[PDB]
Length: 230
Ligand SMILES: O=C(O)[C@@H]1CS[C@H]2CS[C@H](CS)N21
Ligand SMILES: O=C(O)[C@@H]1CS[C@H]2CS[C@H](CS)N21
Ligand SMILES: [Zn+2]
Ligand SMILES: [Zn+2]
Image 1 (cartoon, rainbow, N blue to C red):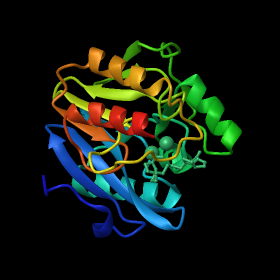
Image 2 (tube, rainbow, N blue to C red):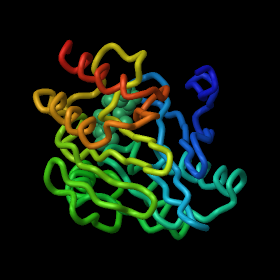
Image 3 (tube, protein in one colour):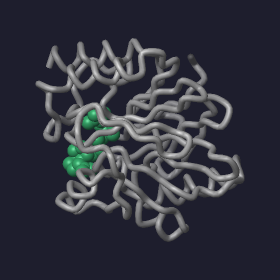
Image 4 (cartoon, protein in one colour):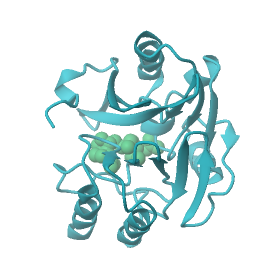
């Protein structure tokens, strides 16, 4: 689109917000990994006079900057956060959120896996997400467990008001042509998990990957192509 913030535009420690729809934003941060710097996305969704945060900004410092940018640009309190899998780009900063008064949530699986990794652990457990195809409402969003993909615990998030599908790290941006980290993945199941995402959200209008530029439902087929080419 030419409007979305890119990795080179954001120094590590800064956070950008991108308005997607009425009461729906993405947050974009950057972090060092494997000798390079990469971007990472999360989501912010308005719920009346409060905000729901989806995912941290990949570390304590970035997450503090995220909260500052939210206060500056939106001016509504973040009351709850959901982490969509156990990796540091999703949970790193949970301790900062807790210290800011945010109630943090993740599935039982995500909480267990974060503990095993030595990552920060979201406090509260999400009910009703244990089996592939499970969906639950959580304030202004639906949470969906599509099955194992990028990780065994990965969730996706849908915002019905705007037909926004937040795929998280189970969905790759269009420009990515090779697999990312796969030690936690289920490459055999990933294409089927993507089929379940599309079956549940076949009218999604905007699809946000965990890293990089948003797209449409074409990102699902693209991700399958990448996973199967690997
Ligand atoms: O954060 C993690 O749990 C793990 C540890 S090793 C490395 C692989 S993917 C993710 C970085 S986004 N990561
Ligand atoms: O493993 C991944 O899918 C993603 C996308 S590419 C690779 C580098 S940035 C981020 C850190 S976990 N990552
Ligand atoms: Zn991940
Ligand atoms: Zn990620």
